[PDB]
Image (cartoon, rainbow, N blue to C red; front, top):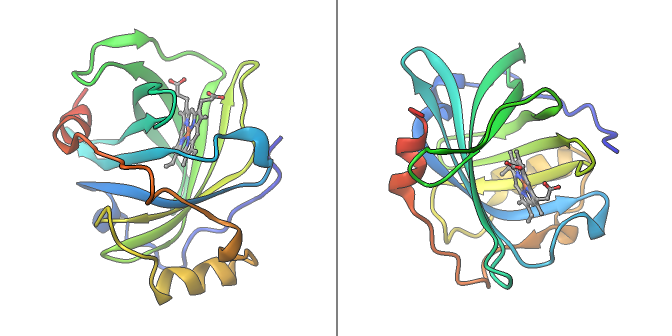
Length: 184
Ligand code: HEM
């Protein structure tokens, strides 16, 4: 179960975040710990495509090799706070699992600048829900979390020390597929 009403960044700059580029997850915190594996790789692209607000997601479990992509259109609840109805696709945008009622995530940008961000997401997916999940993002897949984003983690009354890093997983991404999935 999700439990947090995450607060969006004051003065969030939507066009800069949703610029069509890629964000890498460098660290994550699942509130229900056995909710997700202890080793993971995830990234997204976020942009407007033909007037529509979009995200493309990539998940990879580096131990099992489980891999999946998703595309969503985001609807706006308030500045920096969205509800997204996802379709599972291959890397080329071919639909594997269509959009359906009940399959959605919420997405809140708690902090962002040109290079880093802190987000919250709540996944709803039939009998495969996840609880609250926070992620530190960077434009550079190898960047250690800096002071701006770590201060934002503190300001959210979270302990960065509890976040799990993705950096020791040999994560390798297909940026081209994430960018082109925005259109799909
Ligand atoms: C970056 C922000 C993230 C968003 C918006 C997000 C969103 C999603 C969505 C929409 C799905 C379902 C996809 C489908 O069935 O087609 C999913 C599944 C999953 N995600 Fe994430 N995710 C993110 C990051 C992460 C991270 C960092 C982890 C763990 C390190 C993670 C772990 C999982 C797992 C294990 C599943 C499959 C299990 C399930 O569907 O219940 N995700 N995620």
